[PDB]
Image: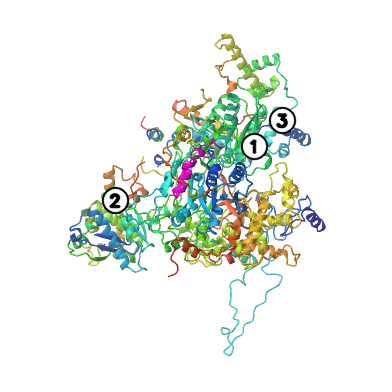
Amino acid sequence: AALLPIAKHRESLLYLVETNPVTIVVGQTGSGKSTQIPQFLEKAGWCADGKLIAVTQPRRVAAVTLAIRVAEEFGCEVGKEVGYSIRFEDATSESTRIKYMTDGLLIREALVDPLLSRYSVIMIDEAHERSISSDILLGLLKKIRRKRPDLRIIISSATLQAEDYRAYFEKASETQEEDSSNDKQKESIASIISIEGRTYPIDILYLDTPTEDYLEKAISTVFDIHTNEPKGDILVFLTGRDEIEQAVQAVSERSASLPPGSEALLPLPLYSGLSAEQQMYVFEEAPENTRKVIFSTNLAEASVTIEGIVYVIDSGFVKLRAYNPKTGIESLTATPVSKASAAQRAGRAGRTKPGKCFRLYTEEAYQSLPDATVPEIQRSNLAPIILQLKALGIDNVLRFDYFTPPPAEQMTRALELLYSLGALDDYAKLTRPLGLRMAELAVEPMMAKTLLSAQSFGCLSEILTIAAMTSLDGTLWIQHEGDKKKTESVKRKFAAEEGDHLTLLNVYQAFVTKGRKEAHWCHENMLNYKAMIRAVSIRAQLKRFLERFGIDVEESLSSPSVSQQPANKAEKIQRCLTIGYFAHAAKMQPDGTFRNVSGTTVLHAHPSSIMFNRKADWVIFHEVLETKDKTFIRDITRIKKEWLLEYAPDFYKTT
Amino acid sequence: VKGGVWTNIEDEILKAAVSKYGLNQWARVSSLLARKTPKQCKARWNEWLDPSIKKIEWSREEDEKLLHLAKLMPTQWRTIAPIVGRTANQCLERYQKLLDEAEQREASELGLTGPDGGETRAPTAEDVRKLRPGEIDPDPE
Amino acid sequence: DDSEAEERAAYEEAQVRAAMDGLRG
Amino acid sequence: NTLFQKDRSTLSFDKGFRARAEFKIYQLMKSNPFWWTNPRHDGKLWNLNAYRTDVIQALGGVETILEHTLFKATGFPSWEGLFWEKSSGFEASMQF
Amino acid sequence: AIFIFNPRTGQLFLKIIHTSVWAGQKRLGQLAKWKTAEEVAALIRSLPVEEQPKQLIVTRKGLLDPLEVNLVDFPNISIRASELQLPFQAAMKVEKLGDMILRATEPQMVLFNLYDDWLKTISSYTAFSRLILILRALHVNQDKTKLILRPDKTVITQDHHIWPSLTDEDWIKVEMQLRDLILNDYGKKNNVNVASLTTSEVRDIILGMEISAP
Amino acid sequence: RAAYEADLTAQQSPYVFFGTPLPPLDPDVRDDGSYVPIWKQEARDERGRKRFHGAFTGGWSAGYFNTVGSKEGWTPSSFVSSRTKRWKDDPNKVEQRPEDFMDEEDLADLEESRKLQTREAFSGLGSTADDAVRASGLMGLFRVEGETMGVKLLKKMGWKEGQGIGPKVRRKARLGLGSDANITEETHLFAPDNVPMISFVRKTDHKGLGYAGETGLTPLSKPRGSIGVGILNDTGSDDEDPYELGPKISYNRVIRLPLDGFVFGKEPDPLISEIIAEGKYPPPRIPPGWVSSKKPSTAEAAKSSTLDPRARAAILGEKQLPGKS
Amino acid sequence: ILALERLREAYSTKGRLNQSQREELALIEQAYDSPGTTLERIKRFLLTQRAFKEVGIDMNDNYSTINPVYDVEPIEKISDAYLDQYLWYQADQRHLF
């Protein structure tokens, strides 16, 4: 720990954080900023008064890994002195001093603590990753620092755009210009401190011509660099899961044809939804006379650091989520990388030994990419963040100190979405009874509107369970490629024709009522364990939040009262859904496809719902996303037309 | 996908289908195979799977007959093939192989090339006929 | 461009020589 | 007017279309009744539009032609502003 | 003169600026634009909300800036820059308009009807196209436009009308006469044949869109 | 049937407590709910026989078995009124709607005609219609956005089209007089301009960066209507322009050794150079004498968090939007 | 270009095409999309491939005479259409006829 460059400049950063209100540290990931800076401020004595230090992270697994790493380095247990909080997981205590927080959860705690009086210094590590919540934290910390200069702010910058960060801290406000009459020197509120890192020299290699098909030249580069150069673990950054699947199949087939007596190649994938076994296979080092070839998506960049890696092949493409507001649909599209992205690519290439970089594009092309990533608030749903900013109380969303301005018409679509869910009035003000109740939840707003309409109409706990399991990213069903009719049967073991939501409700009621919280039962049923018990905890949190809404929870699931007919109750559930999901309505077309109300965009059923292979007439979907070729819609549920005409009188009308 | 190269599964299913349906109903036989048409099944039987097809290495007598007939009837290969005793593609590829093999032994005799271990070898016409990914074979049967 | 103009002029001369066939020469 | 076609340069490379169109009868079952003329090279060798007007004038006018039919049983005031649908949705739904 | 034209109704608002405004002032274009924006704002304030416009189309891009200063209290009125080279200036070439502009001693509101009585026969789009064609031809040639608009002494302009009264067919005759004159002038200026200008190109020339060479 | 479908449905899935479980996968019973393209479907009727039943829906029989009547018959209604008792002052005046003279299929295709469309004041999903409207010239200048009311409430709260969202900008102007900096620069309060939207190209391929690619060719050029030739007897378009051949033609008016195949970068990446280097700025001086001033639940607080956003913004000092006034 | 439309004049846009016509239409659209590879394949076939597939034969009935109609494999049809156009063009410019 003493060999890190962060220890040499510890006194300088301590002076700059004790004197200046805000100080911007510039350094790359791996120089020990996030591991030692909370330790340095704790050893300086910034928690002697019961005040806390927080680290705002964009990634969740990175937060957990850095929490356990700093807990191991500090010699303390997780949560008692160094703790963390990610979404619906708060390993924290009163005795805990160092906090590793989700920045979105500090939005939700800015719904709790107005002046942030429970924390001394707030720091945003790897701020050039640029999440939405990081930027809105930047705005609110600027406002609070005008309101309360006692707290301190640290921003970790990857590169020179800290100067732009610096720019954001001279333009403070405009009310101070009336009081700016004296000839006093403008004090350095914001300062910059240098902590460099340490990387081995890395050779960069380009191509004389633009590449034809980056998968085939990726694998041919892998095999050529295996045959020519000596031992070193080959890593390649690909784009999406089918690309890594095709790559590992191709390298396995070619390694089948390799001449004997040489070093064997072990193909390994790296994804987001990996199980424990192959992730540990990647983590464990290469065996004797064996070289690991690891194909990775965007995990080895900053989220999970893998060691002993020498070679790295850059495909030049990274997938980005964007949100078109005119059509109003998501899109998971393969964008060219940023110069900062290929920069961190080359930086993470040569970690343990002087390595090589294999950017598969020309040097003039390398000059031609943009310098930084596309701003993320220009390509995202502004509806939940406008909802959150109204929940804080800043209704004047037009006159707010953003770091970058969002597009002028995307937020119009956002607030139109807010009005369609109620929430906002005709006069752009949050409604007291309903709007706050959709506001303070950490759930997607449309199904929050679904949840808050249940009590006035009837059944609530069932769609509460659905809200528990829709706030969940990794899929329930484990992907066993050896079973095709068997996984189809065990889906049909739980499936119902009235939508995917009823199937999820059935799997939850099978797990809870009779399953006795037993993991191996999910092991025969091709079901996950950790994410779905996390969803159980999510259901507990939602039930508690509704308990502070003052509405009594009708927990009739434990009661054997089945005297109500189940067909009308399923109709009640899907009717509550179509009250809450009236915007996402589609009609099935006899070529098997789905079209919107306007009949322009082509939508296909996602290949995970049961309605992928079923007949339907009118449907609602939890989400819609445009992939590279086809637009897929997710969590299909059956509806009826007159329901939509009844429950959306302002939004639908007959011909 | 309604194309590809013939696998062992497809050849065995084709022979059992021919055993059941005969040699005059290729649409039933092609209904058995997912990737193959009636014409492709018929071409596979006629060019490969027919038990009158000699798949052994050639004799010198058949070489003499093949070169003699290819001189008699230029590029009339479907005429030459019944007389020689093989199929048309077999006779064509053997004739091309014999010309290229004579070319390589002539190039060895005239001695332009030195040792046979350098990369400066003259690329042959057989090196041109090599299928790349995304390319197809004219005669997969 | 000049190449397209040359080929178009060749077409126009072809149509003329198809129309003038039989009477001048 | 064939001197003013949109694509003339590509048509400049099109030779032998008359012998080729003669020999197309050994390649296709559908006999082409206009084998002799090629509209890109020869041009529009006739025009029979005026016939339509005259045949209406032969049959007693639009008023007489429509009063043979159920036009007046449809509630349509005037014949202008109308169109015929080639097929209903039921017909296109059952075609395949 | 400051011109404000309504294409929907044909009402023309004229604001005359005297030499007394320019007396004792420096950087005359700057406060000229500022006074133009201020007079537009004053006319908007004078007009009722029902008669208030919803879109302002300016022939000059710089007018985007000071009008935003003068329309803080009226956000609902949109300001858009015109890429078209609209011939709205050429209205100085009218004898009546120039005669009353040059003889004005005080700044005043002036009301005019540019469509005269075209609204009773043709639509506002056709009248707008005819007015744009007439202004473009006036920018091309004032005397030739005067000769075409009044080919005979029998055609007499009314007292309350700016353009001479003509029938619809005579107006159509004047329409392609002015179209031919504008096309001939454009062909003389740009060395492009009249036939090679297709209908889209003719409409772009009439609208004054800056035609980009291939 | 009956017993078999019931007990194998009970055997395959007792776990579907809510809704209805899927019918069993068996060679005996059929899966009616599964999709079966359109080139696999059989055209059957309500009864379930492969048979049509209309004059214009492909049947050899129309009406109630080639009869205009019905099974129930038809009975007219009585209607008596006079001076003492009139029909129009009756309490239950049964009006004559044009729906008691309709059959069930008339009602069916009438509600089939009643399409659903989203309202004009709210944008629906994928409403792609403004592109042809805007690219029309004067028509796009006169025709405006269809006043989706989120835009007009944004106008109400103080926003204007043509510029974006952010804090007030204290920029003077651009008068259009070149770049003259000799203006007094008294800097009125303005609004930030809109950032352009990102329109990302569709990437359906693994083509590399900077590759323009092999260019693709183009095909060589290219009282309203008729009764029709049937949808099966159409084959392919053997009903052209009956008068003249050919599609109409568009008419012009006038006539260390690196890896093989890999090039070496001539200049290094700047930030793989500054990672070794010290940066562009020095650390602070830190003179001796300065000393440190200080010497070495969330859920429960959220339960008692009764602070409304109005008082929250009051104690946080943020300006609020004007309400109803 | 020319060769492609000749083949596409044989098939109306609509219709009940069997398998081989839709394979031919796929090959024609593929040739339009990727012309360089198509031309290189045509020249490779024209140099190298000397053994060809079966050619279907049927009769067309004019009620007074019947004539044989030969149905050729589509990819060889594209190669022959290109060769036909090239030979007619070069025969015209070199004054063969």
Residue A396 vs A22, above or below: the answer is below
- Residue A508 lies in what quarter of the image? bottom right
Label of residue F176 in the image: 2
What residue is pinned by disc 3? B45
Residue F171, given in percent of the width and then of the height, sits at: 34, 53
Label of residue F153 in the image: none
What residue is pinned by disc 1? A283
Q: Which amino acid does label 2 sit on?
A: Gly
In space, the residues marked 3 and 2 are separated at their CA atoms by 82 Å
Residue depth check, mark 3 versus mark 2: number of the one nearer the observer = 2
Q: Which amino acid does label 3 sit on?
A: Trp
Residue F195, given in percent of the width and then of the height, sits at: 42, 50
Residue B61 vs A138, above or below: the answer is above
Work out whether residue F200 or residue F41 is closer to the camera in this orientation and state it.
F200
Marked residue chain, label 1: A
In space, the residues marked 2 and 1 are separated at their CA atoms by 63 Å
Residue contact at pointers 2 and 1, CB within 8 angstroms: no
Which residue is painted at 22% across and 57% down in the image? E92
Residue depth check, mark 3 versus mark 1: number of the one nearer the observer = 1
